Length: 109
Length: 109
Image (cartoon, rainbow over all chains, first blue to last red; front, side, top):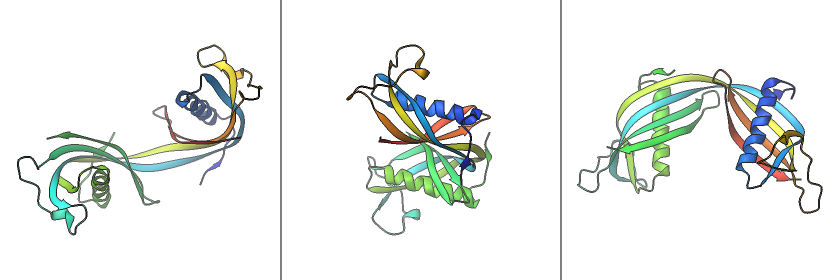
């Protein structure tokens, strides 16, 4: 994984100032806090794949608690059916075999 | 930016099943929802740099609302001083000039 990097390095210093900026902004403290000591600084290049999916999604008549969900019929009754257009952004790191849902938003159709 | 990708492609299908999985888990709905139609599927390789910073952070006597904060003296009074060891993880995409704080946790020292 990650490897040691000098704090003198512009990237490491920029990231430190930034993190301490965010820590400060998120705090409920009226006092400014700042670094006493940097105990360790490491860094790692990462590549990944973003998928950007525009998908219409529809409500089915199966409950989440039952078998064979992936070709289950959509509701057709007046106040039961629901359809939305969703935008999903998925960040995959394939050597790791992981996926994260970075972004998710829908509008009723 | 991103480029069109067939839904037949194992990566695109895996990401779709995953997103719809998450959408379902996050919902308050007892019914299963599923894709009616995939309107678009695009994908983009991204590289970035994670910085992993272990930093002791100390409370200063300046307020957030005043000048010259970065060599301001630490509190020394009994119930005013505070010190913590923090772990920050910063995700940088340097062509874009952005940084995000992916992870942030501290323990009082």
